[PDB]
Amino acid sequence: GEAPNQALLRILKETEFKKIKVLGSGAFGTVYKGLWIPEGEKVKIPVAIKELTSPKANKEILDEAYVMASVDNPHVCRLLGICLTSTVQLIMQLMPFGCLLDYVREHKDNIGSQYLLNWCVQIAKGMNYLEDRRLVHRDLAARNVLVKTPQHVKITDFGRAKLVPIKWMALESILHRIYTHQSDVWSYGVTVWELMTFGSKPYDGIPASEISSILEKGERLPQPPICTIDVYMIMVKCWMIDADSRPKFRELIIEFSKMARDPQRYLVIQGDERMHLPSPTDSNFYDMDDVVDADEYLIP
Ligand SMILES: CC[C@H](C)n1nc(N2CC(C(C)(C)O)C2)c2cnc(Nc3ccnc(-c4cnn(S(=O)(=O)C5CC5)c4)n3)cc21
Image: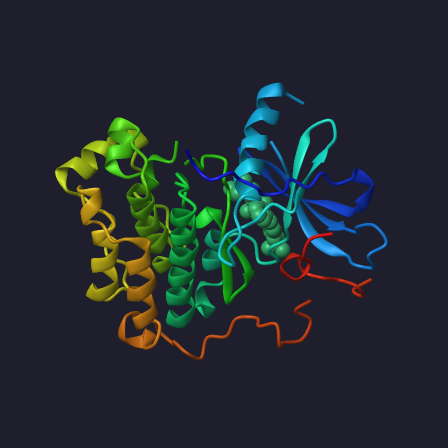
């Protein structure tokens, strides 16, 4: 059959989690900001703690734990461990800049072409990795891309990942519930559109029930003002009826990489290049002592 999944599920003690405060709540559940202080290791890891006491809630979150514990890529979010309390909690890496959707909306005036094109390469890299691991995300959107640093993004939310977000879904998925890596490619094109429009809602005001009809007639999301025909043509290719005619994620990495070498040729932004976003070599970016990021804290 398939290859044995030898990933390790780390059961973490409640007593090892300090300075807990709410980051956000919604349909997704509740995400808390915390500090993981393991054993006598002299490390304080900034963490995010997710929870959806119901047996069906524990089933769904343990399915997300299963997928999230099985992934290992710089552009994908890995599970650090789980905490078994009244409800099952997922322990993950704190992404200080939150989701990419809210980031593009709040920092629109300082987001340049190089940042936008790099985010596209990075999302495609993480997506290609999921394809290698034979995983179909089934919920790629700008809301599910987290910002570690303005120059480093990662894909998350494995609640729907396998081996309804209508406005992000490929037409085969809306009509026949068919999900493939090529259906994820359609969602990637919508994710790209969301970025290029600085967080615009796709098909705003249009009800979900009308989307399938809109797509069948031949209607697609419009060309963002900053997008050259070069960038939009890539988005359009992700939205073709025939899934096999859509680009492969490895081709999106190549296409956006070439473009990111001359970003002003592919994205037209007023007051470009001069736009600055916080870097790790800048003041007040970071007890403070013994703080180690999850990407630098390997195994026990
Ligand atoms: C995505 C929204 C979630 C509430 N959230 N908010 C953050 N903070 C906002 C705060 C400021 C204001 C300072 O910007 C940063 C934040 C930081 N790290 C992680 N960490 C991770 C890591 C891996 N996965 C997840 C994860 C998985 N599912 N979800 S979700 O269901 O909340 C997603 C659909 C929104 C988050 N979170 C998640 C974070």
